[PDB]
């Protein structure tokens, strides 16, 4: 280990791997808040070069929370293919970056190589990547899963129907579902964040979602995004199980903040296998995002990019159908503006794909962040070129109860027709038979929720 | 181990399995452009990206960099400024950079010689380094050019926070037949000492357009040497007074 | 017309069309400097709504500099197809936006409709478009031209080789040419901005460019980007004529600032037809960019988006092979940061394509702007999805000489392989013969200028 | 210059380039009438060899009417790319023939090379070409233009609807239009030669044509083939402008015979740009044919093939949408029989394509020529293999007021289905939606004008 270079004659010294990981980040508001950011542009570049010259072994053997003290660290470390690790352990992070980006590196090459990574090493690669590096790197690392739809095939682009309501009103949820489907949204999942966290309400919202699914024989899956214990409860007691959701955090302390034990996610897998209406082998759904560990007190002096990578190492253990970052869900204190939210979105998606999870992005912002809808549209298109597995859909992107702006139903149809991308093949076939889609494109009759009536 | 600002970092060949590596070195020798750094897929190699990022961090500082008032005083120069108060306002308000402040007008009438044939103005503009590196090389042989065989020479003076169109107002107040402005053009990624000369015959604020100016650009040690450029600008000034014309209105 | 709307109970009144056009702009530092920007987000939206409800006739009949006072206005107005105009003159700008964006509007529909437009109307549509509107709208309006390459075919993506040097040193120009061609850059043009402005030097720079073109039988064209008069001088005296270049401005006073008469561009067309080594019927090359009219004192109270649209109306008269905006060429006083430069890039490109010119973009920034290379990479990819005809290439994007950062040779290869786009078909054939490209992708021995030796 | 060879021991001497051009022609009745023909077969071959050994400079620098005395000569000469000319000026006509015919000569090679030609040089190449030379040579020189249809794409074949009537009866014109469209004729133009040359009648015939076009939303264009001044008059006063027509002749004296000044064709271009209902950039329509200069007194001792080539050099200046020779329009005094009319048709089309105009042919004969309908069918098929851009269509080819026989509506459908050629792609799409065409072929319902009722 060098923890040291000289830049324009000036010696830059850092204390540990954790500080080098933190200060190599592009400027964001969360790293300044965490106290972990570079003091200058020159120290940023010095941290980047130190990181680049550090080896895979250097980063692997210094996780940001230690093995003994953290079950997520344990889970990440114990999932390593040590044969894959031993092949690459004396690679520099510079060499690993160039390996990932190389056109002579195949999907099958990275398939084995990523098994020798930990999340800290995944983070380290992203930190010395430019924006086009993150986009091209992610594009050449497809991850494909299957529920009742197949997601993540190159040339395809999926979307979550997010039909949220302030009262969980079943007419208002159904209204937004019919609108979303008319734009070809919902092949990732039809997924409601409920107001109330109880079995009767969970089951009623699931009955509404699956009422629509069963009437029109839609190849998709439903989800209610309450706490994982309440989902399991509802499904055991006979509510239709589709995807099972949990928000996750990249430390044990962060999971405790969220009220999650790892054995709940074990249980969710087993409940999925017994109960859930899923043709394929993946039925889990996680959401993540930069800032959450820092909110929780639970980052332990580590930056939010490294902590967010540790989400993906956690998620990978459970082989979910879908994961998305919710990239600007929280506010300006972690990511301040357009530039920071785009960069985070590209980082999050690259790191997800490098970790080998089915990685999408809620391209989003809040009204107290320095941000508008043109940022969502910038980011969703960049990420779609990166082969982002899915985004969200809401009516014009206005969430009326989560109080933020995500992407429109329009935006998925736009991305698909702009970039010549198709839905999930199962869902596309359904859209064609409904008269909503022809040759990847919305028909004249599309965009009209009254088609279903 | 490598400093990214070193000559070894600058001379780096990154092309992985070369067809002809002796050509590669002599191509790298032929230019200051970032050639021969190779690729990883279609993307830049890591060291090439790192040195790019290092050079940009250095480049950002040079736009905010200001010369000492004391350095201007040590050159024997009158310091005058524009309407701009500070570096941050300079970058956002070019219209105020194109006008002398009220105290600047009165200082020029006080302290400078009246109706010169040739008036040399010097301004930091967008790069202080372009002035400070180049000044002693360019300015003495420029003054000794316009004097020795020739003309009524103005006294040279610094304008702080100057944009190019300010030389029209300087021409009107001082009655100058030719105004030469030596000014810092905006900083490149890997250099900051690029000076331009902007020079104009007998200008007027209402009536002079940009095409009426002759530009001599890229004056530095990696461009046209400041000593060599000094005799270019004198010969330009002599041609300007002969023809009573500057810029696109000049012959040949 | 109405100059007036009520928004949340408050009346928003504007003086004229010129003010409505200006305040409808997304926030940029140039409109604030010009004194013409909206005072708030609310007055911006009110301006947008007033603009959207104004007819095509309202904006056609109020150009921002009047017919009798301005030769660019005269050129734009006299080029109108009045039959196409009369069909659309009572359309609102809201209706024209929706017409442009509609999937039931074909390339051939817009081909006739755009002939009824003026530049101010073209500006008016862009002003009420979102970022995704600008990208999708531009994409469904391809513009194809032909020199020795064909540019602008959907599924293709071209690049100017920009081999600039601080002394116009012929070894340094050559080195940058060989590097560019090895990445597949140069199908738009091989185009040098010269230091000295001067028939001996112009001919020597052109001899260097065409030395490489003739040796390897490259389907492309050379250009030297001095003032148009010295180009014409040099070509008349027997230097190789490829593309003939001029920087243009969207008013008569702006052209006078640049030292340009309209009859010089007539002459350039005539000199092209007599002298130039061009197989196709297009041989002119313009560059543009927001802020230039405001710099010249020549915007006449109009915003820089409306002025930039008028560049394209001027350009369209001369049917050039290529035009690009040089989007962040000048600095922060006209476009301050990432978000403003992206927005302007998308506006400029959309407006060019709506004006029916072969529109590209120098995705660029300066070092005194609030901007870095990640912005260039963001913008180049967004614009490539919009079907941007071409970008620049320089070695890592570093101009050693014009003192700014544009896109890398890398970046064109990245865009093409990310988005499954090809070069100009003629240039692609050449790259295949040289062993630089197979199936749209750089071969192993690409990226290496020693291939040519 | 040699003006001399020896053939079988016998010395053949000619006076000038004009005599060599004249006597190298294949035997036709017009050259004998002009007094310019070869006296024997041996002198024909001797003239051919002298011509073949003469250089491009020899022919260019001796036009058949001099620069000072003739505005068409001036127009042809002043349109030369002199750089293209200088490359080829020391080529023999033999070498230029072999260049044109070579499979190693691309479309883009000839694109530049033809710009260094004049019409006399174009004529000289055709004179030493065999019939298969003329056909294969023309086939590998496609010329593509666009009005509301694209014409001249390889693999396509277009047709003029020629619905002429003895009284300009609007029911009889409409009848023939409906019949023509049912056979897939009219993608070149729907074009009436009127009886009476006045604005009210012109406008009424245009209203009838565009009545049909607008009702069925047909991608095509209308034309009334009166004198160009009367067309301009009608269109200014508010008649629908499609294509603007003029018959042209290859000398200034010939234009004066026709009542044409060049500034009328300038005006027609500008009137097109202001008024005309045309999506693409080409809106002019010329007709030509061998014999017209000789009729006019206006050939100046030159043969009719050279004079007809000069039509195409004139036409090329104005970049028309379409040109056709009307190959046997006049009578036996210029082309006597089947063999001469076929040869002229092949010459005319080759020379048009070499001149870079969108060249078709009215394959036709008169009742006082030694000719019948089997000649029309011979020639139309040969020319279709040569990539003739269009022919005419009339009901069985019987023109009831121009008193000649052109090609049937049947003949375009025959050629298309024989040779696997399609209409203009825009027009083909319309035919498919009308149920007239499937896969390039007439449906069962086609050939029936009552389909439109
Ligand atoms: C930025 C820039 C521009 C901008 C200027 C807008 C602005 N507000 O900055 C735009 C895009 C408008 C521009 C246009 C052109 N430019 Co310029 N420009 C530059 C650049 C990169 C920076 C100059 C600088 O930093 N000035 C210093 C600052 C402090 O001055 P400023 O007050 O803020 O800006 C003023 C000057 O930049 C001036 N200016 C800018 N370009 C030119 C060109 C000429 C000939 C003149 C007299 C003045 C001039 O206009 C501004 C005042 O309104 C230089 C390259 C370089 N490395 O210097 C080329 C450069 C000066 N440009 C050049 C040329 C040729 C042109 C054009 C004539 C191109 C063309 N073929 O039409 C046009 C027309 C210029 C005009 N007559 O107005 C050449 C000059 C060659 C010469 N010795 O004559 C240069 C050196 C680049 C090159 N090709 O090598 N340019
Ligand atoms: Na934005
Ligand atoms: Na016959």
Image (cartoon, coloured by chain):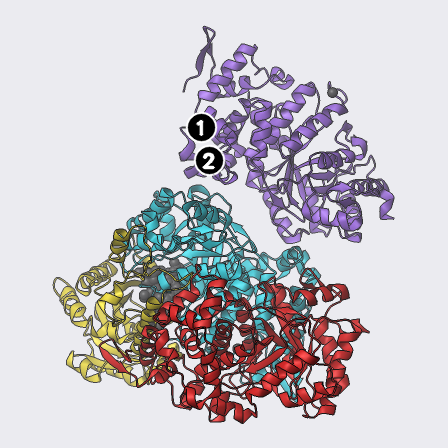
Chain colours: A red, B yellow, C cyan, D purple
Q: Position of residue C330 (x, y in %)?
A: 40, 70
Asked if the beta carbon under badge 1 is closer than 8 A to the nearest atom of ligand 1, the reply is no
Which numbered dot is residue C405? none
Chain where mark 2 sits: D
Q: Which residue is mark 1?
A: D56
Q: Which residue is mark 2?
A: D116
First in residue order: circle 1 vs circle 2: 1
Task: Answer yes or no: is residue C319 visible.
Answer: yes
Q: Are marks 1 and 2 on the same chain?
A: yes
Q: Is residue B174 above or below residue A292?
A: above
Q: Is residue C147 left or right of residue C51?
A: left
Which type of secondary structure does the marked residue at label 1 adopt? helix
Q: Residues within 10 Å of mark 1 (few under 14, many from 20)?
A: many
- Label 1 close to label 2 by CB (< 8 Å): yes
Q: Position of residue A256 (x, y in %)?
A: 53, 93
Question: In 3D space, how far apart are the residues under numbered discs 1 and 2 (Cα atoms)?
Answer: 9 Å
Q: Position of residue A351 (x, y in %)?
A: 48, 75
Q: Is residue B123 above or below residue D274?
A: below
Q: Residues within 10 Å of mark 2 (few under 14, many from 20)?
A: many
**Quarter of the image that includes the N terminus of chain A:** bottom left
**Quarter of the image that includes the C terminus of chain A:** bottom right
Q: Position of residue A397 (x, y in %)?
A: 63, 79
Which type of secondary structure does the marked residue at label 2 adopt? helix
Q: Is residue B161 left or right of residue A169?
A: left
């Amino acid at each position: 280990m060098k923890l040291k270079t000289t830049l324009f004659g000036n010696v830059y010294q850092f204390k540990d791997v954790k500080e080098v990981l933190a200060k190599a980040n592009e400027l964001r508001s969360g790293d300044v808040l965490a106290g972990v950011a570079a003091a200058s542009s020159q120290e940023r570049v010095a941290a980047k070069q130190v990181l680049s010259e550090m080896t895979v072994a250097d980063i692997r053997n210094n996780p940001v929370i230690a093995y003994e003290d953290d079950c997520v660290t344990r889970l990440i470390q114990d999932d390593v293919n040590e044969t894959a690790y031993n092949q690459i352990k004396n690679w520099s992070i510079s060499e690993l970056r160039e390996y990932v980006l190389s056109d002579e590196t195949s999907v099958d090459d990275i398939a084995f190589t990523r098994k020798g990574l930990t999340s800290e090493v995944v983070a380290a690669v992203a930190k010395i990547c430019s924006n086009a590096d993150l986009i091209y790197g992610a594009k050449k690392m497809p991850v494909i899963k299957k529920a009742n739809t197949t997601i993540g095939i190159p040339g395809t682009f999926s979307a979550r129907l997010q039909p949220n309501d302030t009262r969980d009103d079943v007419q208002s949820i159904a209204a937004q579902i019919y609108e979303g489907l008319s734009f070809g949204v919902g092949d990732a999942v039809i997924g409601v964040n409920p107001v109330t966290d109880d079995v009767e309400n969970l089951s009623r919202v699931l009955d509404t979602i699956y009422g629509v699914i069963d009437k029109f024989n839609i190849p998709t899956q439903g989800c209610v995004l309450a706490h994982v214990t309440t989902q399991i409860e509802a499904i055991r007691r006979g509510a239709p199980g589709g995807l099972i959701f949990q928000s996750i955090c990249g430390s044990e302390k962060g999971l405790k903040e969220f009220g999650v034990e790892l054995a709940m996610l074990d249980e969710a897998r087993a409940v999925g296998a017994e109960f859930n209406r899923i043709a394929g082998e993946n039925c889990l759904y996680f959401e993540t995002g930069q800032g959450s560990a820092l909110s929780a007190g639970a980052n332990f002096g580590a930056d939010q990019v490294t902590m967010e990578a540790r989400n993906y190492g956690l998620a990978r253990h459970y082989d979910p159908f879908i994961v998305n970052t919710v990239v600007g869900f929280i506010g300006p204190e972690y990511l301040y503006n357009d530039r920071q939210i785009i960069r985070a979105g590209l980082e999050d998606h690259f790191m997800g794909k490098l970790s080998g999870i089915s990685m999408g992005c809620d391209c989003c912002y809040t009204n107290h962040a320095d941000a508008d809808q043109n940022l969502n549209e910038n980011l969703m298109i960049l990420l779609a070129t990166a082969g982002c597995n899915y985004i969200m859909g809401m009516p014009l992107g206005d969430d009326i109860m989560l109080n933020y702006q995500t992407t429109a139903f329009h935006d998925t149809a736009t991305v698909r027709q702009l970039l010549n991308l198709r839905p999930s093949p199962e869902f596309e076939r359904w859209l064609e038979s409904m008269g909503i889609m022809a040759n990847g494109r919305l028909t004249k009759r599309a965009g009209d929720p009254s088609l279903f009536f | 181990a490598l400093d990214l600002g070193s000559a070894e970092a600058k001379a780096w060949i990154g092309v992985e399995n070369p067809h002809r590596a002796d050509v590669l070195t002599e191509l790298r020798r032929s230019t200051v452009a970032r050639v021969c750094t190779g690729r990883a897929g279609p993307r830049p190699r890591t060291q090439a990206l790192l040195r790019f990022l290092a050079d940009h961090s250095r480049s950002k500082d040079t736009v905010l960099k200001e010369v000492p008032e004391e350095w201007v005083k040590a050159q024997g120069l009158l310091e005058v400024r524009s309407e701009i108060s500070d570096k941050n306002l300079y970058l956002t308000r070019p219209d105020m950079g194109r006008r002398l402040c009220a105290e600047a007008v009165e200082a020029l009438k006080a302290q400078c010689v009246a109706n010169p044939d040739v008036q040399v103005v010097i301004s930091d503009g967008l790069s202080t380094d372009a002035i400070t590196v180049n000044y002693e090389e360019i300015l003495p042989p420029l003054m000794a050019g316009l004097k020795q065989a020739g003309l009524k020479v103005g006294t040279p003076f610094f304008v702080r926070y100057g944009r190019v169109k300010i030389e029209d107002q300087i021409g009107e107040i001082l009655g100058a037949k030719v105004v030469i402005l030596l000014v810092g053009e905006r900083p490149g990624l890997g250099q900051s000492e690029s000076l331009s000369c902007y020079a104009v015959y007998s200008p007027r604020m209402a009536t002079t357009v940009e095409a009426d100016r002759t530009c001599i650009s890229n004056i530095h040690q990696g461009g046209t040497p400041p000593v060599e450029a000094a005799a270019v600008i004198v010969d330009l000034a002599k041609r300007m007074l002969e023809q009573k014309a500057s810029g696109i209105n000049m012959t040949r």
